[PDB]
Image (cartoon, rainbow over all chains, first blue to last red; front, side):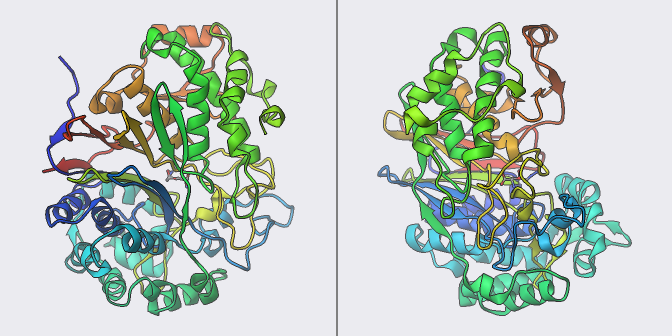
Length: 350
Length: 190
Ligand SMILES: *[C@](=O)([C]=[N+]=[N-])O[C][C]([N])C([O])=O
């Protein structure tokens, strides 16, 4: 009957971009770990098998919902360096230099992944950090086979940055070329880092050897991340943004992410239509949705920022009254140029 | 970008979206740590009115500042039905993370598609600026005439996102789906 069928399981399940990492997640669940434990193990596993995005030197968000309904969000997003400045990415003419914000040592923010994972693990997990990091440790120490995804990413995107730095090239390049499908990727240095974290906890990263290595890498190349930055970093548990769509409650990430707010905003807008009637792929459904999104991105550019620095009008943005007023400016048989759309007037919704 | 979801035997659930930002970030390994460094600083508004790598714009709210966390679009998400965790999803895609998650939710609730169907369905997206109705291959030539007609400027492009989702049956049974757009991925359980 269906053309597409979901994978089925009766006890636990993990879905991720990498087969090895997913399997790491499942094995942890089978050992009696909880969703959070598995999630941290998967996160450390990806930092090794999916260096494209999985990481220890990046950041992100996490939404946790207990079996009892308790829903919370962990913000382990990166903090700009204390010595970071407003116009730091401007050239002499005062124009944004993409190279500076994407490839130089100035593009980096103090990483929050280790922090966020440990916060979630200590408060919501049940396994010690050393146990959930072990799978990733072995993968880095003993290596793994490069698959199509990694091989393709190394060639297409890796080529533009990895071979330009000696330590990076030594790890991901082989015989003057990016590792190919079938080659083995061993990350001895990462294994040592992982091994140290599993032993001295998250401080190994923000205060220990790893912190030193990060600070020196920046200092010797014009970066700003100092040991004070790494020591002054902290993951932050925040209240999820949520809404109600046709009787279903939706929970997502609140600022610093703009994710939560706008997904809810658009759903509120859409609620004012009989979407089901139009059906998937229909001309109408695509019409309505395309327009609703416009207003959201408009508001995004204006009202969204680190809540610890700016006040976001999230109540008004997710206010159904406002959403209903946005819905009316929508014509099922005619669009509205992004030019004739500006950040909404949240006044009567404050 | 990458997102993963987990649900255990007790019904606890976690959705995580994390990244270095662009693929491999700056491509700079921090000394002998073996750790690649992110280029998340580009998510800040380098200059009010000027778009970043994803075409996203900002002002003073998202301008560069010390100890400030740059604006993100990552959306690990959880939908609840009849008071119970029902859908756990999310996806990479910079600015498209928002409309990608949105379509997963709309596909599940409004069109009654199973998590695999909802995942394999074609996607579209509009971020105000640039002004265009970005689409993926998979939408009928006919339906597309109406968008161009009704007024939209359809712009076919690269596949959007990599949803990794799990749906929870009323009886505790788990249903999952990995995105066709990402190869070598996996949704497994026991
Ligand atoms: C990721 O989707 C990786 N890519 N391209 O970017 C996410 C972005 N940095 C965000 O919204 O935080």
